[PDB]
Image: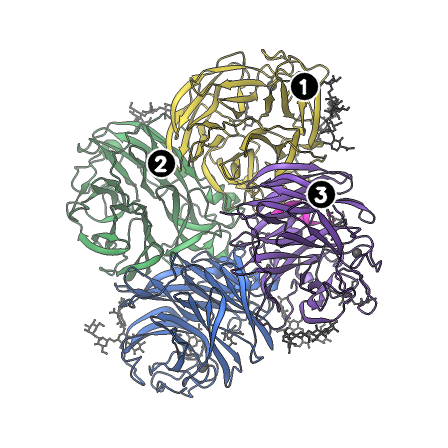
Chain colours: A green, B blue, C purple, D yellow
Amino acid sequence: VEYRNWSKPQCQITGFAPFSKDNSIRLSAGGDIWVTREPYVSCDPGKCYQFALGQGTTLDNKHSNDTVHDRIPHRTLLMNELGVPFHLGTRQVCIAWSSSSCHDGKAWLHVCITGDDKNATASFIYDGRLVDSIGSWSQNILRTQESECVCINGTCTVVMTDGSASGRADTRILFIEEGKIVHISPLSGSAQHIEECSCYPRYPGVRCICRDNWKGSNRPVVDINMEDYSIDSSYVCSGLVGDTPRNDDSSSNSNCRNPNNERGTQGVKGWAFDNGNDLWMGRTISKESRSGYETFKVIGGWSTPNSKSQVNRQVIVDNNNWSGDSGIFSVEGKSCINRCFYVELIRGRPQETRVWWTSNSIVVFCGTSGTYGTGSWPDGANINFMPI
Amino acid sequence: VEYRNWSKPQCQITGFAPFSKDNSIRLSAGGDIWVTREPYVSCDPGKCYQFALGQGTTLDNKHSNDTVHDRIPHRTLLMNELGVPFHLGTRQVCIAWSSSSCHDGKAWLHVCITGDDKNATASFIYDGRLVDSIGSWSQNILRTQESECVCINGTCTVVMTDGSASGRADTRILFIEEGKIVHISPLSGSAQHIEECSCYPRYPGVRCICRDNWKGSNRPVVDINMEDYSIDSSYVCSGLVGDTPRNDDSSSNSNCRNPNNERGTQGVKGWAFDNGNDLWMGRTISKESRSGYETFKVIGGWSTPNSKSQVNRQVIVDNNNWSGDSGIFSVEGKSCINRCFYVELIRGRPQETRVWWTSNSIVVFCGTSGTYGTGSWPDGANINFMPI
Amino acid sequence: VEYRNWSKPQCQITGFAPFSKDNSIRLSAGGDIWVTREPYVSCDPGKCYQFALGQGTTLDNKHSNDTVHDRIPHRTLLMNELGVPFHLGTRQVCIAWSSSSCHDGKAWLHVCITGDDKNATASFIYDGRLVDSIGSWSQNILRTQESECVCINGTCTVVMTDGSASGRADTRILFIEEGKIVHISPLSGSAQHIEECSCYPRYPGVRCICRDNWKGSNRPVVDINMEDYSIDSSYVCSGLVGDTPRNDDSSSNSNCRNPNNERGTQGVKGWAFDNGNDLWMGRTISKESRSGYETFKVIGGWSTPNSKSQVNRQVIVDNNNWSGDSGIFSVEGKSCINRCFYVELIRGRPQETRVWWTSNSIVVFCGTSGTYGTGSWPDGANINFMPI
Amino acid sequence: VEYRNWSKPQCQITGFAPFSKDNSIRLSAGGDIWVTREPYVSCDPGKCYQFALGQGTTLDNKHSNDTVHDRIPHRTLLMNELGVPFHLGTRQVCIAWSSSSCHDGKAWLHVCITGDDKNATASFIYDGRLVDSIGSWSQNILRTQESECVCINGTCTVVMTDGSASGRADTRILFIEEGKIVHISPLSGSAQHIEECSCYPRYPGVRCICRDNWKGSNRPVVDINMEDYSIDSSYVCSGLVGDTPRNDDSSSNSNCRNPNNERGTQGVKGWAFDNGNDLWMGRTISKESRSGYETFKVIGGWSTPNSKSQVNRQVIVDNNNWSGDSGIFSVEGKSCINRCFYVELIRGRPQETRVWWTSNSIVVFCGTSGTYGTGSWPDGANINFMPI
Ligand SMILES: *[C@@H]1O[C@H](CO)[C@@H](O[C@@H]2O[C@H](CO)[C@@H](O[C@@H]3O[C@H](CO[C@H]4O[C@H](CO[C@H]5O[C@H](CO)[C@@H](O)[C@H](O)[C@@H]5O)[C@@H](O)[C@H](O[C@H]5O[C@H](CO)[C@@H](O)[C@H](O)[C@@H]5O)[C@@H]4O)[C@@H](O)[C@H](O[C@H]4O[C@H](CO)[C@@H](O)[C@H](O)[C@@H]4O)[C@@H]3O)[C@H](O)[C@H]2NC(C)=O)[C@H](O)[C@H]1NC(C)=O
Ligand SMILES: *[C@@H]1O[C@H](CO)[C@@H](O[C@@H]2O[C@H](CO)[C@@H](O[C@@H]3O[C@H](CO[C@H]4O[C@H](CO)[C@@H](O)[C@H](O[C@H]5O[C@H](CO)[C@@H](O)[C@H](O)[C@@H]5O)[C@@H]4O)[C@@H](O)[C@H](O[C@H]4O[C@H](CO)[C@@H](O)[C@H](O)[C@@H]4O)[C@@H]3O)[C@H](O)[C@H]2NC(C)=O)[C@H](O)[C@H]1NC(C)=O
Ligand SMILES: *[C@@H]1O[C@H](CO)[C@@H](O[C@@H]2O[C@H](CO)[C@@H](O[C@@H]3O[C@H](CO)[C@@H](O)[C@H](O[C@H]4O[C@H](CO)[C@@H](O)[C@H](O)[C@@H]4O)[C@@H]3O)[C@H](O)[C@H]2NC(C)=O)[C@H](O)[C@H]1NC(C)=O
Ligand SMILES: *[C@@H]1O[C@H](CO)[C@@H](O[C@@H]2O[C@H](CO)[C@@H](O[C@@H]3O[C@H](CO)[C@@H](O)[C@H](O[C@H]4O[C@H](CO)[C@@H](O)[C@H](O)[C@@H]4O)[C@@H]3O)[C@H](O)[C@H]2NC(C)=O)[C@H](O)[C@H]1NC(C)=O
Ligand SMILES: *[C@@H]1O[C@H](CO)[C@@H](O[C@@H]2O[C@H](CO)[C@@H](O[C@@H]3O[C@H](CO)[C@@H](O)[C@H](O[C@H]4O[C@H](CO)[C@@H](O)[C@H](O)[C@@H]4O)[C@@H]3O)[C@H](O)[C@H]2NC(C)=O)[C@H](O)[C@H]1NC(C)=O
Ligand SMILES: CC(=O)N[C@H]1[C@H]([C@H](O)[C@H](O)CO)O[C@@](O[C@@H]2[C@@H](O)[C@H](O)O[C@H](CO)[C@@H]2O)(C(=O)O)C[C@@H]1O
Ligand SMILES: CC(=O)N[C@H]1[C@H]([C@H](O)[C@H](O)CO)O[C@@](O[C@@H]2[C@@H](O)[C@H](O)O[C@H](CO)[C@@H]2O)(C(=O)O)C[C@@H]1O
Ligand SMILES: CC(=O)N[C@H]1[C@H]([C@H](O)[C@H](O)CO)O[C@@](O[C@@H]2[C@@H](O)[C@H](O)O[C@H](CO)[C@@H]2O)(C(=O)O)C[C@@H]1O
Ligand SMILES: CC(=O)N[C@H]1[C@H]([C@H](O)[C@H](O)CO)O[C@](O)(C(=O)O)C[C@@H]1O
Ligand SMILES: CC(=O)N[C@H]1[C@H]([C@H](O)[C@H](O)CO)O[C@](O)(C(=O)O)C[C@@H]1O
Ligand SMILES: CC(=O)N[C@H]1[C@H]([C@H](O)[C@H](O)CO)O[C@](O)(C(=O)O)C[C@@H]1O
Ligand SMILES: *[C@@H]1O[C@H](CO)[C@@H](O)[C@H](O)[C@H]1NC(C)=O
Ligand SMILES: [Ca+2]
Ligand SMILES: [Ca+2]
Ligand SMILES: [Ca+2]
């Protein structure tokens, strides 16, 4: 039982291969399955787990009505082995309407936020016990990543933001050792309006690609120095931008430094990672709505502003199907650290009004150095077959 | 593995942070979930478990009718990891309409009482086998804590009562080693009625805050010497009293020694713990019924008779929602012993007569030395969605 | 991991204390629960398991119709931790309409009989793999204990019968090492019909109390020598006889040697055990049907022919409620080997014709050297509340 | 833990004894159970697991409609302990409409194929992580064994085919070390079409008996050299042929070398294994459809062309009941390697059109050196009791 250091090079991938799918909504029409949203994946050194925020109810249940609402006291963090759908034997790890989890090589850390919008509490649970907590600092919806945190040599880091809703984002980067907060660093650099960071180890530090909670369709970047707690930040250079809504590729812009003002309505959590000068990224296929999902490599997408040449595109979910939040997780291999991602497949409200609930399933892909084909792996439920 | 000694100082807490919630009743409307009451939480050295007394039936089941009653032969002690709701794969640990459980560092002890009101049997199960038993000594509902027992150096102590619910009874403190009763001591001291003790390690001894069902709305205290088996008892000093029913805050009293004779008949299981001269305690918000739940610190609440200065109040369940029993459990951290509590959230009878059943969910909080905000975490089920 | 030898004295027993109850039938009215019969209990060195023969269906299921029949190809041996009811996640350990199981200290042996009445197959599965098998030797319902087998120093023994249910049959005692049949001994001694033996370790040998289905309401005894494989047999001395049907106590007899010819046809699986000259035993309360269940000690019940002085009676199931098969299991304590028993609580056909199925729950008690009270712990389902 | 080498002789067998049955379809009428097909069994060194390809739905679920189709994006590989039916807590190990799995002594390998018919992807998951992938090489339904792969000394081998189902195709044998493809060998030898290989260790190599879907109703054999990666192939010598369809026993033939051109188009997955010059094999009882299942030894069936002398026949499923795929798995005993097999019991479409779904249960038998009787162990569901 040694601490993870993630001190291997990043795997040099050619694209992604199918890893997992849970079929939650299809099963929900013939079984008792939790209503969820904001899922993610994180792995201990041996095996992977799927997480999501429950809505305190199963789908075929009158309490499923109005589950489009983001925050209620009954939301809890669910945790199963990856591919075990959220059945009634699922453990609720903590009370949470916003969360992040990660394993440090020895045990699990869970960051769980619940309570009043104006005065939330974040609990820090490590190795099965509550070790620390912090209250809201801006009194305006304290929130965190909705994907895995990252630990190096026993110190885990997680990004949180309070006050972005009111246009006064106060973003802080926490450093946590065995559940205890040992340092808090304010955001520094040129990133603004940070929400929902998707972070990954990039030894010796941690790098996050997030979303801008005002009008940037280009994604913020946060760099975390684990040695001295210093922070820097910017925007992804790629002219093929990662958020939705967004302009078409021809009329999209990013200068690597500032938000581009090219998204007019609420954006979506997503991810990307650098490989030298290039950038691997995912995004919705639609530029208007959370439908479809595609991945590709942008040539110069990390280093060159407004870079727009891509290669190695893959469709994950075709544009006739709903997507949602997406995020990165990292998995240690023999010789390298691999990058994987999940896609939230949102069903029900607001897009599908036959039913009165909102829930999701997931699909999960992992980096590969090998070869692969094509397909599309959507949620797959028939909305007309569902309990309403 | 080694026996627990709990020989660390008590954590110096600033209040409590959210830890767990099971949503049992909301789930029961769309899933097969046990009917329960008298829940509690207890942890082995690695992880926490939720316990409750089943009623031998699920909620959506005609057998859930009449479950307001406390004692039937079909009640069994249920045990799951904390946050796993009581689904059909839940283990029934023993036959019990009253119970207590605890882990000594090596194995679980369960104390399970069942049978005739006039002639009950308590079974003592340790490390998976029945080791001892004792029969009723007063022929009037032999009964115990309904929360965790406490073990130091391999000796587990539990408080049991037999006799009148509305007059002098026969309370005994048992000392149990690897499931075998090794000593039994009579209650001594000035407490006049003892039920449903909430006990905690206070090395080298154990301290319990209980329910007086006869003449006191102040809570009795039992002090257990684990070295020589001597017993003392008194009442919590705080003029802000912990039982329900009770007088309002302006007219309630305690003198630390005698029951206050203030709405003293009846009561509810609850808890408190000392910190120096001060007292941390929970209670229902209502002074009349099991409605709402709040915690606070009483300055001088341990040492000073009739102290009423409070600080650090937190609402756990607002007064528009039902509560129920509550109890303490203790969790060993790196440097100190933390105190946590659960609240039973009773739904159905007698308060909600639209349905014919009585069941509960739970919410659980743990001490923190950090900061926190506010909220309310009630059961959350809509009584009108439930099967009757 | 060492082999069990059971080489400690039998525990002092003053009677029995409640240990477990599964509430299977009550749960079946609001949940997906297996239809079963022929249950039993057996423990590995750390924990106990409940076993039963499934009927290849849940109760609330059209396939539950006409499950009164004892042998169909869909019967499988179910195995859960004791107290975990037979939910849909239950493992089916082998195909079986008759079975026995036991743990040798290192791994589980299962003896599983299935197939045609006139040509059945017994499979021997050990440590998760099929190691041996034997075919029917008398072409008339090869069948075994329906309770735990017994292992000493890595050799497990089990009693099996083939041939007439109402006349002379061919009973053999098998000796099995790591799943392999290493010896077979014919039944010898004065027992004239042996079925459904309830066996226990009495180091260095094994002792069984069985069912005579032909000529006796007194129970046969089989003694097994594990050193030279020799077998002896006789009848329990007690004039308070253990089978059902039987004469009333005033006209019932046993001479320790021959079947009593007192309502000697038919019968039910049961148990007893010796303690010096005395006998601890269970039986149904009714002398006509499988109704009620009582235990008591017969003074001289082991050594003295026709002894009828009983003491220490306990009602387990009152005579207004259905019972069924019962059997013994043994549990190793720190200093002695304890004796426990289970009772099958049969519900449905043929006694209860409102429903079309037959199933059971269980209740389980363990020997105690302590004290205890009284009660009754029947199945508890309301036949009117059940799916038919 | 050490790598498996399977370096023990094959167990003596006299026939097969009952091992497991899951009753999936019977249970589906009163419980939430996955719709599946293409099941198989594989064991780690300690215990066995059942696998199958889910259809992304339970049976009693409108999404079960039209699950006769073999490939949709929602198919995932399910894995439970053997005998645990596919309930809602079952883990979906990967996305797959064709699969193979095996344990190398240290960890599990899963080969999972999904995506577009003309451009599928195979993922290779080992020890809980994606290690490699390969894309379709013939752009026509990349597909694999639907039963266990085989590993010797840390190298696992699996047979895969891409191309026509009704003409020459492109079959390759992969060699995989800790999830990484280290070599790929083209099919060589006289086998003209290879699908759905049932492979087993035959130290120092691996031997496979497969399905020729083009010109043969005799089963092809593939021999795999694990040391130098060389491949040979032929046909099973037995004149009693193993595919369906096939000619009757009087007019069927095999010459060991070439497809027999006897009702050679179409087929079903099955198995056989050698013992010296003799052959043990299973097949459907019907020569036309997947009805019934029988096993027998063919004297000289491995070495003598057109041998038809069968002996030691056993009915596994009588010819009034549906069967389906069947396959081999191998289990290491104390001194020898045993051979076992499973039979898929297909219910629903296309044979049973009362219902709109297609699913299966399983029955499993293992080699025995002992004796046995007779029986028939079909699926057992009443099609008239099923949800449609
Ligand atoms: C209770 O259960 C048991 C176990 O399940 C069951 O016993 C099995 O019964 C089946 C059905 O009868 C047996 O399977 C059949 O075997 C038939 C062949 O067996 C005879 O021929 C064998 C081969 O002979 C050829 O080869 C030899 C050289 O090897 C050569 O000399 C011969 O001339 C010939 O060329 C031979 O090996 C075998 O020998 C055994 O028995 C003889 C006595 O006769 C003995 O001397 C030997 O020592 C040895 O023990 C034997 O002579 C085979 O024809 C038959 O297949 C046909 O019928 C089935 C239908 O049944 C058709 O489907 C099929 O298409 C064929 O037309 C089948 O394979 C099986 O062997 C038994 N198992 C065992 C272990 O004994 C009982 O019957 C059950 N009891 C009841 C009443 O239910
Ligand atoms: C966000 O979340 C936090 C944490 O939950 C909330 O802060 C908590 O608020 C409650 C309610 O106000 C506090 O509990 C109360 O404490 C007072 C006692 O303190 C007051 O009176 C003291 C003299 O008796 C005085 O010294 C105090 O002022 C000093 O200290 C405070 C810090 O404690 C500091 O902020 C000041 O600057 C001073 O230095 C203070 O004025 C107690 O009287 C209350 O009990 C009465 O009221 C309750 C109802 O509120 C009633 O039910 C009782 O019967 C009784 O009549 C009560 O215990 C608690 O201490 C705060 N916690 C912390 C850690 O500060 C915060 O309010 C939330 N904000 C929002 C907007 O949601
Ligand atoms: C079988 O599967 C393989 C593997 O998935 C697949 O090969 C891939 O094809 C895609 C599409 O041609 C390639 O990705 C493209 O790369 C070019 C650069 O060479 C880019 O210009 C492309 O982007 C443009 O076109 C996209 C639509 O295709 C637009 O969405 C985008 O906005 C741009 O306009 C795109 O990135 C990919 O590199 C290969 N992968 C590999 C490893 O070769 C193959 O096509 C499939 N076979 C068949 C018959 O379809
Ligand atoms: C949940 O269980 C409760 C408790 O059983 C049940 O409520 C009860 O319903 C029964 C009727 O089924 C009521 O029975 C009556 O009790 C009164 C006394 O209060 C008697 O006087 C009645 O007897 C008269 O009516 C009979 C009708 O046949 C006549 O035969 C008889 O001669 C008398 O005229 C009768 O027995 C009982 O009062 C209630 N109890 C309560 C608490 O309401 C309830 O129905 C169950 N719920 C569900 C959904 O099934
Ligand atoms: C509280 O619980 C205790 C313990 O269970 C219980 O004491 C037990 O009472 C029974 C019944 O009196 C005792 O068993 C009897 O022992 C006498 C010999 O002393 C026998 O003669 C009895 O057998 C006859 O009577 C039976 C009916 O009781 C008949 O069924 C039988 O055929 C015989 O005619 C019987 O064995 C038992 O010894 C005590 N146990 C102990 C440890 O003292 C007590 O009665 C309970 N009290 C209440 C109020 O419920
Ligand atoms: C969950 C809930 O309804 N809580 C109420 C509570 C209960 O209704 C009551 O205790 C049950 O017997 O009632 C409380 O408030 C008082 C009421 O008893 C009264 O009817 O109305 C009063 C004011 O007009 C007063 O509010 C209480 O016990 O505190 C209030 C609580 O919300
Ligand atoms: C659970 C139950 O109903 N038990 C009854 C029992 C059964 O009804 C009966 O044995 C089933 O056939 O009946 C008993 O009561 C009486 C017998 O003692 C008597 O020998 O026969 C009577 C009828 O002729 C009568 O039924 C019993 O077996 O003890 C009593 C019991 O409560
Ligand atoms: C499970 C079952 O019904 N098995 C039948 C089987 C099937 O009905 C049939 O193969 C499906 O197409 O039919 C079999 O017997 C006969 C055929 O051999 C014959 O060619 O045609 C008959 C009239 O239709 C009948 O089908 C068979 O394949 O062996 C018999 C079997 O019990
Ligand atoms: C063994 C037993 O019946 N315990 C019950 C006790 C006693 O009735 C009470 O303490 C008086 O003795 O009351 C409860 O706590 C209660 O009030 O809700 C329920 C609990 O089941
Ligand atoms: C293999 C088998 O069928 N065993 C059955 C036996 C035998 O019928 C009986 O011992 C006569 O031989 O009866 C039972 O125990 C019984 O009476 O309830 C049920 C059991 O299933
Ligand atoms: C990947 C795939 O589709 N495999 C399917 C194969 C192929 O159709 C067949 O081998 C011809 O290539 O047939 C089955 O085995 C079958 O006949 O029941 C079902 C299976 O799902
Ligand atoms: C059970 O089966 C019997 C015999 O076929 C039949 O008469 C009865 O109606 C069935 N019961 C139910 C509830 O379907
Ligand atoms: Ca009181
Ligand atoms: Ca008899
Ligand atoms: Ca063919």
Element type at mark 1: loop
- Name the kind of residue labelled 2 in the image: Tyr
Who's the residue at 39% across and 61% down the image?
Answer: B3
In which quarter of the view is residue C131 placed?
top right
User: Would you name the residue on which mark 1 appears?
Assistant: D299
User: Residue B10 shows which numbered tag?
Assistant: none
Residue C243 in the image, given as x and y percentages of width and height: 76, 59
Q: Chain of mark 3?
A: C
In which quarter of the view is residue B192 placed?
bottom left
Numbered range of the magenta stretch: C61-78
Q: Is residue D367 left or right of residue B151?
A: right
Report if residue C237 is visible in the image.
yes
User: Would you name the residue on which mark 3 appears?
Assistant: C185
Please tell me in which quarter of the rendered image ligand 14 is found. Answer: bottom right
Q: Is residue A261 left or right of residue D175?
A: left
Question: In the picture shown, does residue D327 fall above or below B2?
Answer: above
Who's the residue at 47% across and 84% down the image?
Answer: B214
Question: In the picture shown, does residue C139 fall above or below B23?
Answer: above
Residue B334 in the image, given as x and y percentages of width and height: 29, 59
User: Marks 1 and 2, Cα distance to the nearest angstrom?
Assistant: 58 Å
Report if residue D28 is visible in the image.
no
User: Marks 1 and 3, Cα distance to the nearest angstrom?
Assistant: 35 Å
Q: Nearer the viewer, mark 1 or mark 3?
A: 3
User: Would you name the residue on which mark 2 appears?
Assistant: A293
Q: Chain of mark 1?
A: D
Q: Is mark 1 within 8 Å of ligand 1?
A: yes
Q: Is residue C380 magenta?
A: no
Residue B51 in the image, given as x and y percentages of width and height: 47, 63
